[PDB]
Image 1 (cartoon, each protein chain N blue to C red):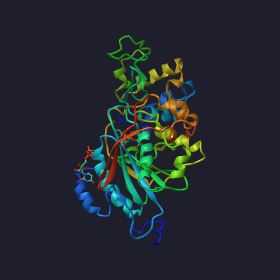
Image 2 (image 1 turned 60 degrees about the horizontal axis):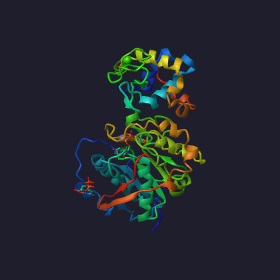
Image 3 (image 1 turned 135 degrees about the horizontal axis):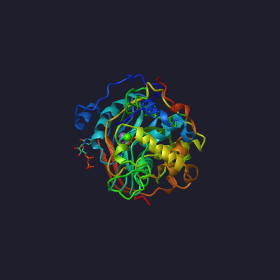
Image 4 (image 1 turned 180 degrees about the horizontal axis):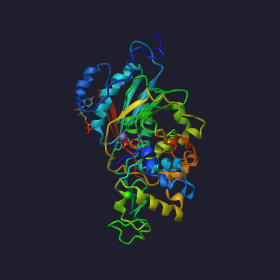
Length: 123
Length: 272
Ligand SMILES: O=c1ccn([C@@H]2O[C@H](COP(=O)(O)OP(=O)(O)O[C@H]3O[C@H](CO)[C@@H](O)[C@H](O)[C@H]3O)[C@@H](O)[C@H]2O)c(=O)[nH]1
Ligand SMILES: O=c1ccn([C@@H]2O[C@H](COP(=O)(O)OP(=O)(O)O)[C@@H](O)[C@H]2O)c(=O)[nH]1
Ligand SMILES: [Ca+2]
Ligand SMILES: [Mn+2]
């Protein structure tokens, strides 16, 4: 489900500020990470990244093809492909606390500057 | 024998763009009798200062090309450009390489005519207003500014994908585009970086005359998201000195001249 800056911004409120990242930065990171698509699925190196946040099945969620994974977030990866962002957010929160914002590789190169353009301009 | 006016008197402004009614290239050659073998057109009324090679990165997108040709040919003429159409068809089945093909388009089109301007255009983008001129400006020009795909908004100020135009010099100044981006994403961001690291800024038509339609389509096999893009994009400054025009290698497999365009099939290697 292709969301929009503002939709993302409103569904993502609870994560604002956590580990010091604002909603401007998340909007920017999320656009470059999954084009705001909650059903985004991408391969990398023998692993898959799921949903809006592109959480990896390598260590964070359980995928049927990786029952070995640490599943640090304790959730089935498929739960990151629906349109309920609560669990995606809680998992993103764990990643932030443990590995940090650098898990999202688009952050440094694409979201280090010019953040005002990422604000949602709709009430 | 007098130069073409700065703004073409033939312009129509906003236009209806849709992809439902099938097109017949034969009907298109029909409607566009001035386009000569290879997809070349030169105004016979005035003398355009814009010798433009339009370069389209290509692989299995003939249906999109049909619409592209149908819509753009009338437009480019309305814009009084001395233009040539180049479709750079990637031969083979390994990962798609957009920027590298663009690089090839540059060298190949130059073999034909002494173009001074280069418009790189993807196959699925149709401008919705003919005031959005396909020519070069005092600074690199980003053309596909407001895509229906993005709500008729620039997705981010640093965006340079879709359709852009660089003069021969502007292009030469950045060692051209990079050849090392295999798969989808980031090459356009890298190109963006190359411009800044060379003192160029981006010129754009405003969001209204920059309205554009991208034929709806799903991501193609062999053009999956490049997992390395974000890291490669962080080093543009150094890599642009060693990856570009000066490191380009490719083999021409076939040069085809149809009435509405020139398609060049090339072997550009593999991700290494
Ligand atoms: O199998 C393929 C894959 C790609 N292409 C060509 O490559 C361009 C880009 O691929 P596509 O999937 O259509 O890209 P998008 O994701 O739709 O388009 C935008 O986003 C990419 C990422 O920003 C850009 O770099 C493009 O330039 C920009 O127009 C296409 O339009 C074609 O011209 C082919 O011809 N065949
Ligand atoms: O100006 C043109 C260009 C193309 N065609 C038609 O479009 C086909 C091209 O198909 P494609 O590019 O897929 O050919 P291939 O490269 O695979 O030979 C031609 O054979 C013609 O029937 C045409 O009628 N007029
Ligand atoms: Ca969910
Ligand atoms: Mn496209």
